[PDB]
Image (tube, rainbow, N blue to C red; front, side, top):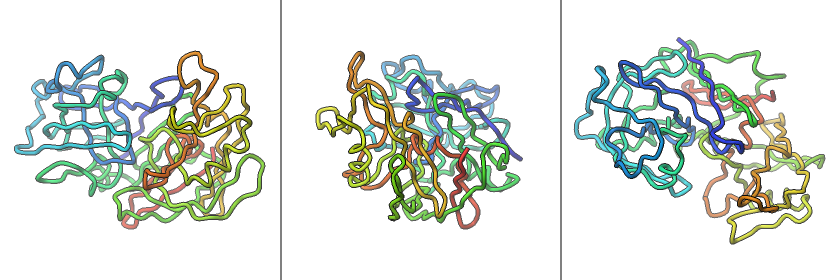
Length: 330
Protein backbone atom coordinates (compact mmCIF):
# COMPACT_ATOMS: atom_id res chain seq x y z
CA UNK A 1 0.00 0.00 0.00
CA UNK A 2 0.87 3.67 -0.20
CA UNK A 3 -0.57 7.02 0.92
CA UNK A 4 -0.10 10.60 -0.27
CA UNK A 5 -1.43 13.72 1.44
CA UNK A 6 -0.94 17.41 0.91
CA UNK A 7 0.50 19.43 3.79
CA UNK A 8 -0.31 23.16 4.01
CA UNK A 9 1.34 26.00 5.97
CA UNK A 10 -0.88 27.30 8.78
CA UNK A 11 0.03 30.94 8.11
CA UNK A 12 2.05 33.27 5.91
CA UNK A 13 5.29 32.50 7.78
CA UNK A 14 5.18 28.69 7.50
CA UNK A 15 5.09 28.49 11.31
CA UNK A 16 3.83 24.91 10.97
CA UNK A 17 2.16 22.63 8.44
CA UNK A 18 -1.16 20.79 8.69
CA UNK A 19 -2.18 17.60 6.93
CA UNK A 20 -5.73 16.23 6.85
CA UNK A 21 -6.22 12.91 8.66
CA UNK A 22 -9.34 10.74 8.69
CA UNK A 23 -10.19 9.23 12.08
CA UNK A 24 -13.03 6.87 12.88
CA UNK A 25 -16.15 5.59 11.18
CA UNK A 26 -17.72 7.56 9.61
CA UNK A 27 -14.55 9.55 9.03
CA UNK A 28 -13.84 12.60 11.16
CA UNK A 29 -11.24 14.72 9.36
CA UNK A 30 -8.81 16.61 11.59
CA UNK A 31 -5.87 18.72 10.47
CA UNK A 32 -2.80 17.42 12.25
CA UNK A 33 0.77 18.64 12.59
CA UNK A 34 2.98 15.79 11.33
CA UNK A 35 5.93 15.76 13.69
CA UNK A 36 9.06 13.69 13.02
CA UNK A 37 10.34 14.88 16.43
CA UNK A 38 7.71 13.10 18.56
CA UNK A 39 5.78 9.84 18.64
CA UNK A 40 2.24 10.50 19.88
CA UNK A 41 -0.84 10.90 17.70
CA UNK A 42 -3.04 13.15 19.83
CA UNK A 43 -6.14 15.17 19.05
CA UNK A 44 -8.44 17.81 20.37
CA UNK A 45 -11.56 15.92 21.31
CA UNK A 46 -14.97 15.92 22.92
CA UNK A 47 -13.08 15.24 26.19
CA UNK A 48 -10.91 18.37 25.95
CA UNK A 49 -11.61 20.92 28.70
CA UNK A 50 -14.08 23.26 27.00
CA UNK A 51 -12.26 26.48 27.93
CA UNK A 52 -9.14 25.09 26.21
CA UNK A 53 -10.84 24.61 22.84
CA UNK A 54 -10.95 27.72 20.65
CA UNK A 55 -11.81 26.93 17.04
CA UNK A 56 -10.18 23.50 16.61
CA UNK A 57 -12.01 20.60 15.07
CA UNK A 58 -12.53 17.87 17.65
CA UNK A 59 -12.58 14.08 17.51
CA UNK A 60 -15.68 12.62 19.16
CA UNK A 61 -15.06 8.93 19.81
CA UNK A 62 -18.67 8.23 20.81
CA UNK A 63 -19.65 9.04 17.20
CA UNK A 64 -17.21 6.50 15.76
CA UNK A 65 -18.43 2.93 15.46
CA UNK A 66 -14.82 1.69 15.34
CA UNK A 67 -13.55 3.59 18.41
CA UNK A 68 -12.63 1.53 21.45
CA UNK A 69 -11.40 2.89 24.78
CA UNK A 70 -7.90 1.59 25.48
CA UNK A 71 -8.70 0.77 29.06
CA UNK A 72 -6.43 2.27 31.70
CA UNK A 73 -4.19 4.03 29.20
CA UNK A 74 -3.13 7.64 29.72
CA UNK A 75 -0.64 9.94 28.04
CA UNK A 76 1.15 13.17 28.85
CA UNK A 77 3.68 15.01 26.72
CA UNK A 78 5.81 18.13 26.91
CA UNK A 79 7.46 19.65 23.86
CA UNK A 80 10.67 21.62 23.39
CA UNK A 81 8.77 24.90 23.16
CA UNK A 82 7.29 24.39 26.62
CA UNK A 83 3.86 23.36 25.40
CA UNK A 84 2.07 20.25 26.68
CA UNK A 85 -1.04 18.11 26.53
CA UNK A 86 -2.45 14.98 28.21
CA UNK A 87 -5.44 12.67 28.31
CA UNK A 88 -6.69 9.13 27.67
CA UNK A 89 -6.53 6.79 24.69
CA UNK A 90 -8.77 5.17 22.11
CA UNK A 91 -7.95 2.83 19.28
CA UNK A 92 -9.61 3.62 15.97
CA UNK A 93 -9.17 3.56 12.21
CA UNK A 94 -6.86 6.28 10.92
CA UNK A 95 -6.21 7.09 7.27
CA UNK A 96 -3.71 9.46 5.71
CA UNK A 97 -3.88 10.16 2.00
CA UNK A 98 -5.56 6.83 1.28
CA UNK A 99 -3.38 4.70 3.58
CA UNK A 100 -5.39 3.08 6.38
CA UNK A 101 -4.29 1.73 9.76
CA UNK A 102 -6.80 -0.10 11.90
CA UNK A 103 -6.32 -0.17 15.68
CA UNK A 104 -4.22 3.00 15.75
CA UNK A 105 -3.81 4.59 19.19
CA UNK A 106 -5.59 7.95 19.06
CA UNK A 107 -4.68 9.94 22.16
CA UNK A 108 -7.60 12.09 23.22
CA UNK A 109 -6.69 15.34 24.94
CA UNK A 110 -8.33 16.15 28.23
CA UNK A 111 -5.96 19.10 28.74
CA UNK A 112 -3.82 21.19 26.38
CA UNK A 113 -1.53 24.13 27.14
CA UNK A 114 -2.28 27.67 26.07
CA UNK A 115 -0.14 27.59 22.91
CA UNK A 116 -2.34 24.80 21.54
CA UNK A 117 -5.59 26.51 22.51
CA UNK A 118 -4.40 29.72 20.89
CA UNK A 119 -3.69 28.04 17.58
CA UNK A 120 -7.07 27.35 16.01
CA UNK A 121 -5.55 25.76 12.90
CA UNK A 122 -3.90 22.71 14.52
CA UNK A 123 -6.29 19.97 15.66
CA UNK A 124 -3.51 17.78 17.08
CA UNK A 125 -0.19 16.12 16.30
CA UNK A 126 0.78 12.99 14.41
CA UNK A 127 4.14 11.76 15.63
CA UNK A 128 6.58 10.20 13.20
CA UNK A 129 9.67 9.74 15.38
CA UNK A 130 10.46 6.26 16.78
CA UNK A 131 7.81 4.54 18.89
CA UNK A 132 10.23 4.30 21.81
CA UNK A 133 9.32 7.97 22.53
CA UNK A 134 5.57 7.31 22.69
CA UNK A 135 4.21 8.49 26.06
CA UNK A 136 1.24 6.15 26.54
CA UNK A 137 1.27 4.40 29.90
CA UNK A 138 1.25 1.63 31.03
CA UNK A 139 1.44 0.12 27.54
CA UNK A 140 3.48 2.15 25.06
CA UNK A 141 1.82 2.55 21.66
CA UNK A 142 3.14 2.55 18.09
CA UNK A 143 3.18 5.47 15.66
CA UNK A 144 1.04 5.54 12.55
CA UNK A 145 4.14 4.85 10.44
CA UNK A 146 5.24 1.95 12.65
CA UNK A 147 1.77 0.39 12.36
CA UNK A 148 1.61 0.91 8.58
CA UNK A 149 5.19 -0.09 7.79
CA UNK A 150 4.82 -3.80 7.05
CA UNK A 151 1.93 -3.11 4.65
CA UNK A 152 3.73 -0.37 2.72
CA UNK A 153 5.27 -1.09 -0.68
CA UNK A 154 8.56 0.22 0.81
CA UNK A 155 9.10 1.00 4.52
CA UNK A 156 9.57 4.75 4.01
CA UNK A 157 7.84 8.07 4.22
CA UNK A 158 8.91 11.33 2.60
CA UNK A 159 8.50 14.98 3.56
CA UNK A 160 8.36 17.59 0.79
CA UNK A 161 7.51 20.81 2.59
CA UNK A 162 6.79 23.97 0.63
CA UNK A 163 8.10 27.48 1.10
CA UNK A 164 5.01 29.66 1.51
CA UNK A 165 3.17 26.92 -0.42
CA UNK A 166 1.66 23.44 0.06
CA UNK A 167 3.77 20.31 -0.09
CA UNK A 168 3.39 16.57 0.33
CA UNK A 169 3.83 13.67 2.75
CA UNK A 170 4.08 10.31 0.98
CA UNK A 171 4.02 6.90 2.63
CA UNK A 172 5.42 3.77 1.06
CA UNK A 173 7.07 5.15 -2.08
CA UNK A 174 9.61 7.66 -3.33
CA UNK A 175 8.21 10.04 -5.96
CA UNK A 176 11.13 10.32 -8.36
CA UNK A 177 9.52 13.36 -10.02
CA UNK A 178 9.57 15.39 -6.79
CA UNK A 179 13.29 16.16 -6.61
CA UNK A 180 16.26 17.04 -8.79
CA UNK A 181 19.53 15.13 -9.02
CA UNK A 182 20.05 12.19 -6.69
CA UNK A 183 19.07 11.44 -3.08
CA UNK A 184 22.03 11.27 -0.71
CA UNK A 185 21.50 8.91 2.19
CA UNK A 186 23.11 9.31 5.59
CA UNK A 187 23.27 7.26 8.79
CA UNK A 188 20.73 7.61 11.59
CA UNK A 189 21.06 6.98 15.30
CA UNK A 190 17.79 5.94 16.93
CA UNK A 191 19.33 5.92 20.43
CA UNK A 192 17.38 9.01 21.54
CA UNK A 193 14.23 8.07 19.61
CA UNK A 194 14.76 10.71 16.93
CA UNK A 195 15.77 10.78 13.28
CA UNK A 196 19.24 11.82 14.41
CA UNK A 197 22.00 12.27 11.86
CA UNK A 198 25.28 14.15 11.33
CA UNK A 199 25.59 16.94 8.81
CA UNK A 200 29.05 17.29 7.25
CA UNK A 201 29.23 21.09 7.49
CA UNK A 202 27.92 24.42 6.29
CA UNK A 203 28.46 27.54 4.21
CA UNK A 204 27.04 31.05 4.52
CA UNK A 205 25.98 32.70 1.27
CA UNK A 206 28.63 32.34 -1.41
CA UNK A 207 31.25 31.59 1.23
CA UNK A 208 33.51 28.58 1.40
CA UNK A 209 32.19 25.38 2.88
CA UNK A 210 33.31 24.54 6.41
CA UNK A 211 33.71 20.81 6.98
CA UNK A 212 32.52 20.06 10.49
CA UNK A 213 30.29 17.40 12.00
CA UNK A 214 26.96 18.68 13.26
CA UNK A 215 24.80 16.09 14.98
CA UNK A 216 21.12 16.94 14.91
CA UNK A 217 17.56 15.76 14.35
CA UNK A 218 15.31 15.99 11.30
CA UNK A 219 12.21 17.50 12.89
CA UNK A 220 9.20 18.54 10.83
CA UNK A 221 7.47 19.70 14.02
CA UNK A 222 10.02 22.44 14.74
CA UNK A 223 9.71 25.65 12.72
CA UNK A 224 13.28 26.91 12.74
CA UNK A 225 16.84 25.69 12.21
CA UNK A 226 18.71 25.42 15.53
CA UNK A 227 22.49 25.05 15.26
CA UNK A 228 25.60 25.58 17.43
CA UNK A 229 26.24 29.15 18.50
CA UNK A 230 29.47 29.31 16.48
CA UNK A 231 27.61 28.47 13.24
CA UNK A 232 24.73 30.80 13.95
CA UNK A 233 27.07 33.71 14.79
CA UNK A 234 28.93 33.16 11.52
CA UNK A 235 25.64 33.35 9.62
CA UNK A 236 24.25 36.50 11.27
CA UNK A 237 27.62 38.29 11.06
CA UNK A 238 26.91 38.51 7.32
CA UNK A 239 23.72 40.54 7.89
CA UNK A 240 24.28 44.22 8.67
CA UNK A 241 22.58 45.16 11.92
CA UNK A 242 21.70 41.63 13.00
CA UNK A 243 22.06 40.90 16.70
CA UNK A 244 21.08 38.41 19.34
CA UNK A 245 18.36 39.92 21.50
CA UNK A 246 17.87 38.50 24.97
CA UNK A 247 14.54 40.32 25.26
CA UNK A 248 13.12 38.93 22.02
CA UNK A 249 14.66 35.47 22.52
CA UNK A 250 17.08 35.11 19.63
CA UNK A 251 18.65 36.72 16.59
CA UNK A 252 16.79 39.60 15.00
CA UNK A 253 17.73 41.55 11.91
CA UNK A 254 16.59 44.71 10.09
CA UNK A 255 13.54 43.95 8.01
CA UNK A 256 15.24 45.96 5.23
CA UNK A 257 17.97 43.30 4.90
CA UNK A 258 18.56 40.91 2.05
CA UNK A 259 19.45 37.62 3.76
CA UNK A 260 22.21 35.33 2.50
CA UNK A 261 21.55 31.67 1.83
CA UNK A 262 22.70 28.91 4.19
CA UNK A 263 24.07 25.61 2.92
CA UNK A 264 24.27 22.40 4.94
CA UNK A 265 26.13 19.22 4.04
CA UNK A 266 24.67 15.75 3.65
CA UNK A 267 27.68 13.55 3.03
CA UNK A 268 29.38 15.05 0.00
CA UNK A 269 26.10 16.66 -1.12
CA UNK A 270 24.86 20.14 -0.30
CA UNK A 271 21.38 21.52 0.45
CA UNK A 272 20.96 25.27 -0.09
CA UNK A 273 18.44 27.16 2.03
CA UNK A 274 17.61 30.42 0.20
CA UNK A 275 17.88 33.59 2.25
CA UNK A 276 14.15 34.29 2.06
CA UNK A 277 13.45 31.01 3.92
CA UNK A 278 15.28 32.49 6.93
CA UNK A 279 12.94 35.51 7.25
CA UNK A 280 10.24 35.11 9.92
CA UNK A 281 9.01 38.65 9.67
CA UNK A 282 8.44 41.45 12.16
CA UNK A 283 8.88 40.55 15.83
CA UNK A 284 5.60 42.32 16.54
CA UNK A 285 3.10 43.85 14.15
CA UNK A 286 4.54 46.91 12.44
CA UNK A 287 8.08 46.46 13.76
CA UNK A 288 11.10 46.93 11.51
CA UNK A 289 12.97 44.29 13.50
CA UNK A 290 12.53 40.86 11.94
CA UNK A 291 12.98 37.43 13.53
CA UNK A 292 15.63 35.10 12.17
CA UNK A 293 15.01 31.55 11.02
CA UNK A 294 18.42 30.29 12.10
CA UNK A 295 18.86 30.33 15.87
CA UNK A 296 21.24 28.94 18.46
CA UNK A 297 20.65 25.48 19.88
CA UNK A 298 22.71 26.36 22.96
CA UNK A 299 20.68 25.30 25.97
CA UNK A 300 18.36 23.07 23.91
CA UNK A 301 20.85 20.25 24.23
CA UNK A 302 20.44 19.18 20.61
CA UNK A 303 20.69 20.67 17.13
CA UNK A 304 17.40 20.70 15.22
CA UNK A 305 17.00 20.62 11.45
CA UNK A 306 13.48 22.01 11.53
CA UNK A 307 11.23 23.23 8.75
CA UNK A 308 13.58 26.03 7.61
CA UNK A 309 16.09 23.35 6.62
CA UNK A 310 13.78 20.52 5.60
CA UNK A 311 11.65 22.61 3.27
CA UNK A 312 14.74 23.24 1.12
CA UNK A 313 14.91 19.49 0.45
CA UNK A 314 13.05 16.36 -0.49
CA UNK A 315 13.56 14.23 2.60
CA UNK A 316 13.34 10.44 2.86
CA UNK A 317 12.69 8.89 6.25
CA UNK A 318 13.79 5.34 5.59
CA UNK A 319 12.38 2.97 8.18
CA UNK A 320 14.20 -0.14 6.97
CA UNK A 321 15.69 -2.49 9.57
CA UNK A 322 18.59 -0.06 9.84
CA UNK A 323 16.95 3.34 9.41
CA UNK A 324 18.57 6.07 7.31
CA UNK A 325 17.75 9.58 6.07
CA UNK A 326 17.88 10.78 2.50
CA UNK A 327 18.12 14.34 1.19
CA UNK A 328 17.75 15.66 -2.35
CA UNK A 329 17.56 19.16 -3.77
CA UNK A 330 14.28 20.07 -5.47
